[PDB]
Length: 98
Length: 99
Image 1 (spheres, rainbow over the protein chains, first blue to last red):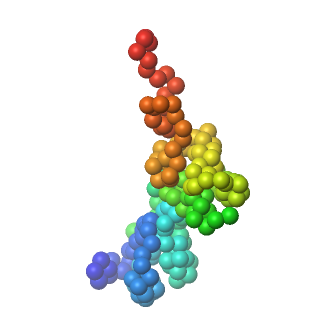
Image 2 (image 1 turned 180 degrees about the horizontal axis):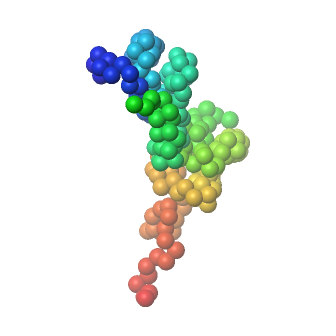
Image 3 (image 1 turned 90 degrees about the vertical axis):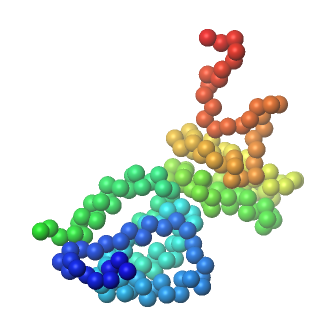
């Protein structure tokens, strides 16, 4: 629904999967399919796991798909204030100029 | 050693409020101490409380006050009659006959 049509094929496409919770196993069955489909569209996904309850397994599964899908894992939400600078630096490194 | 009591020591690692402090204070030594005091325990879940309290105080020393650790856990640090335990009490508490 978001990237249904790539109307800016020259622009980089990135998603922050900021995540802090598990999900029941029955709902995780098509996870790899969707992340691989996003890769085929070259939609980058940067997982940002926060807290002890973050689904680290899904994070590593995302990381396995592509090197640019590198993960951030945070102790708590307040660590976002510390990680923000390098997060934006990485995002703009992943994007081309005009 | 008892699994149900051991969960209480694992609170140091699993709970979000304590997870704030991991960048500053490694919980593993406190978890081991908590496990062996549970082995020494002669009561209920409260036997894990000294380790949690000391971990919270160490974190407060390092800079992070864990405002909510007393609510998530089953612990309740002892206070004199009528007074509530609270993190980050100002030392200049207001007595009536005070300027």
